[PDB]
Amino acid sequence: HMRVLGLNGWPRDFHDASAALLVDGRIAAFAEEERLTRKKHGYNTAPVQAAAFCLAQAGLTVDDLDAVAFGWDLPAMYRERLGGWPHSDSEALDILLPRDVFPRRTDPPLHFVQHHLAHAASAYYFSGEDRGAVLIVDGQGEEECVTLAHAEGGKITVLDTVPGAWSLGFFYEHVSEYTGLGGDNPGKLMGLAAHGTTVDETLSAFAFDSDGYRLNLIDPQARDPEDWDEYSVTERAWFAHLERIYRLPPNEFVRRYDPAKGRVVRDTRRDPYEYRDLAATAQAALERAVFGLADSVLARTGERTLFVAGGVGLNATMNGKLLTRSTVDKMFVPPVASDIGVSLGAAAAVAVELGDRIAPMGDTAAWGPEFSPDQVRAALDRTGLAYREPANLEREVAALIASGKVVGWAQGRGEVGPRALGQRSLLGSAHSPTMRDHINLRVKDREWWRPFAPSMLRSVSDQVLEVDADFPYMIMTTKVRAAYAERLPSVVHEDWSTRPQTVTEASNPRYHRMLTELGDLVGDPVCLNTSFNDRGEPIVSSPADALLTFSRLPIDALAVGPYLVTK
Ligand SMILES: Nc1ncnc2c1ncn2[C@@H]1O[C@H](COP(=O)(O)CP(=O)(O)OP(=O)(O)O)[C@@H](O)[C@H]1O
Ligand SMILES: [Fe+2]
Ligand SMILES: [K+]
Ligand SMILES: [Mn+2]
Figure (cartoon, rainbow, N blue to C red):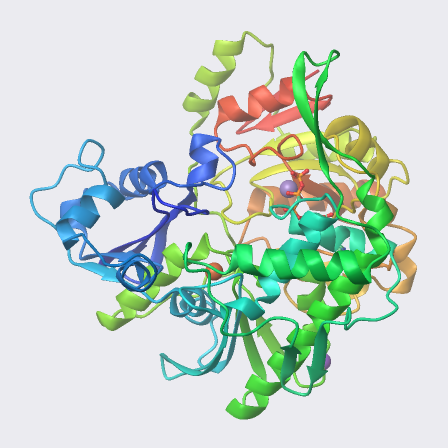
């Protein structure tokens, strides 16, 4: 067996720590550090817990690993930006896999994989497609913010890159920060976009062309000599430019004691909704930039299949429009397009180099921890809450959803990536015209303007959506067909876009059975599926996590394993 543990996350100036374990090209385990630590974004840490989970899941120790793979070229970033790489491989392993958690007789070979190659690998090798164009659109790797590559015969060959200061990723985050939504919540900005109107998608900054874009505002070779990414350099240029061309100045953060909460809370001086027009304009600019990049790499490669990874690959709206583009026939974007995925991608690149063949992900992201009925019962018994073990959990849950109740659903292996896909989900009626406001304002405490997304059977997705394809990851938006746009109001956005999950019997029989039961009740086997967590909070992972969230929120029921808890 070829066993490769892929890692991301490092104690110095890092985010999105994660670990993935490949055994013979298959994902044996994969987790995000934040889910286990409950510390959002997995900042400034080696993926200690995620890696410990991965080994436990597969029943391995480090001595059973053929290789450890890291999803950045770290030595190169230390040599370039920090005056030298001071670690032997052994010292580096001691940092990535601390010996108090990871005892080992000897050191496995350590591989550093160039960051965008790792991003690329996470898309290509898991797509189930033999070849295609590669588009990596990121905040920043070691130097570059964009990579165009050709995937074929199991090789990834880089065609061109874009330097970091021209980052579309940073641009989008800077706008997000500017609006008061936050640089770490660009998904919020994407949601805001449809509520606004675009006048000038250049933002007096971008020039667009057939192959991508230009940013003559920023010197493309600009480097921050005091950090190792160009975030703060781009932040300055973008903030100054935006305050000049846009009617509103930056939204400022307000920190004040709230006597109702007994804490200093952080808020914004203005409502971010006021910036909706800027959001719409930023979204249009990104889309236009990315359309050019994608057309360019597809034409240069002679391919009609497009792979996308990198943080910007989380832009589901953009992904949905790429899909409908005349230059695109098939498209694969992995659930872990962002940096959490470079652990998996580093592991794949190394596994391939070692002669392994990589299995396609196959319509599931479900690779984190799961818990046995006995483990769930211990967590239940700890809280002292009453509960049942229904003879037909799926039918009962469907009935709860049909009646307008909000049901926690914590089953099987935790999903990896930022979307809940029926392993750690909160379920609601897709047909309710009040469900959206209820979950936003009462349950999860989000902005009224945030949209929700549906899970549905692959079998009906042709009738519901304007595209007939698998949408396993909620990473692409698409238009709802006419009859359903008014039938499914809690899960349609301002522009009749939705961000669907299609469910097959194979990928998740339990969820599939549930939706089938739901379709018998409300006509359509579709439900609202938002992630199981308070807004802002990491998706719940453990049964204790699920119970804490269940009890802090006005959720009606929780189906956790085979058990049903009712408020
Ligand atoms: N059809 C659609 N069109 C545009 N945006 C959509 C959409 N469907 C969902 N979204 C948005 O995608 C964004 C998700 O980004 P995230 O940063 O992951 C916030 P979240 O994690 O979904 O919220 P949560 O913490 O309350 O669970 C949200 O703004 C969500 O509203
Ligand atoms: Fe990245
Ligand atoms: K098409
Ligand atoms: Mn969520």
